[PDB]
Image (tube, grey):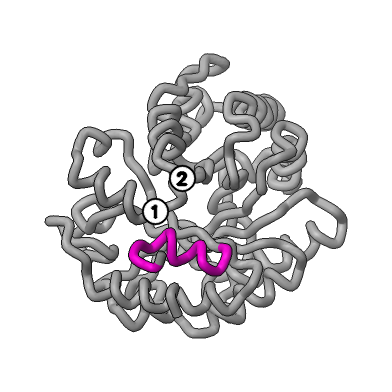
Amino acid sequence: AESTLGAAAAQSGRYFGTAIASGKLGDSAYTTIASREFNMVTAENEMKIDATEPQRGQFNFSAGDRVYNWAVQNGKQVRGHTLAWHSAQPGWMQSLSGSTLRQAMIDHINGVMGHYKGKIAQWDVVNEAFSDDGSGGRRDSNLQRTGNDWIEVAFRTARAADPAAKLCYNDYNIENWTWAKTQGVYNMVRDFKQRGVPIDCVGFQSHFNSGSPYNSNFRTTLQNFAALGVDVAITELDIQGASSSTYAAVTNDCLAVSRCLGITVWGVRDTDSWASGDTPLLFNGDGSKKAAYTAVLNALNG
């Protein structure tokens, strides 16, 4: 196949994934589609820090396992999302600073990766660490305020916690090769690779809209990161208005870069999207395929 997105991606060694939401798992229109079309699953909410460690030291894996087991029973692999992040922190973690927050960050990684050890294809270890103010510099968060080495410490922890997982740095607005943010991250991954920090992948959320338009230099971005010796992934793809041509273009960027592992779109139907008003996904509210679906499919069969 040929007929579905994931089977067609697999023709060139790649995956086509989606974001799954444990709450929509009793909707069978939703699971029929999701099961048929994707070979990769990211839990949309259920593996975030507030979802896995809502009380300090007391982890909660129900919602995460529910998504995990659905995926796995339906033939899919899984991306973990996400271990260290400025948002989606619980109350007890937002209150922490300095070394105590550091210890909590390390503890979270160890615990979450521990529970999922050897069962996760990729982990977004660190998420959205860079700023949008145009400086190319780090976002100012409690995590950053523990010291500039937090990202790297997060990565070394995670490598030791689950040596089988691909470790990703994930971020939005790093798709355009000329943006500061792109270059700030580029420079970090370069520095990492040169010094031997265990980072395996970079995750391009690929949330495209009027404020962050697709640029065909996205292919240059993907090429240049790959050339540092990392894989790349399109992790949270959606496109405001769901242009067929933009959807075919992004798909074709991925197919032209051999270290591009695959594409994940951020939800199944437009009604499931965090931006449902923009109808930015491949399926309509009612389950019918959008033009973009056909364009992506053709490209993957391309």
Visible in this render: residue 180? yes
Disc 1 marks a residue whose amino acid type is Phe
Is residue 227 found left or right of 84 in the rendered image? right
**In the image, which disc is placed on residue 76?**
2
Q: Residue 18, relative to residue 104: is it above or below? A: below
- The residue drawn where x is 33% and y is 75% is 210
Instruction: Locate residue 76, reporting x and y percent.
Output: 46, 45
Which residue is located at x 36 percent, y 72 percent?
A: 297
Q: Residue 290: give x, y in percent of width and height.
A: 22, 70
Judge from the rendering whether residue 160 lies leftward or rightward of residue 3; answer left or right. right
Relative height, residue 86 to residue 244 (above, below): above
- Say which amino acid is labelled 2: Lys
Tags 2 and 1 touching, CB below 8 Å: yes
Q: Residue furthest right?
A: 195
Up/down of 86 relative to 282, above or below: above
Give the labeled residue for mark 1.
38
* Residue 132 appears in the picture as rendered: no
Neighbours of disc 1 within 10 Å: few (<14), some (14-19), many (20+): many
Instruction: Looking at the image, tell me whether mark 2 or mark 1 is earlier in sequence order.
Output: 1
Q: Position of residue 250 (x, y in %)?
A: 45, 75
Image quarter where the N terminus lies is: bottom left
Q: Over which residues does the magenta segment extend?
A: 2-13
Of the pair 108 and 261, the residue shown nearer to us: 261
In this rendering, the count of numbered labels is 2
At a point 77% along the width and 49% down the height, the residue shown is 198
Q: Position of residue 108 (x, y in %)?
A: 60, 28
Q: Dividing the picture into quarters, in which one does residue 191 lie?
A: bottom right
Label 2, label 1: how far apart the Cα atoms are? 7 Å
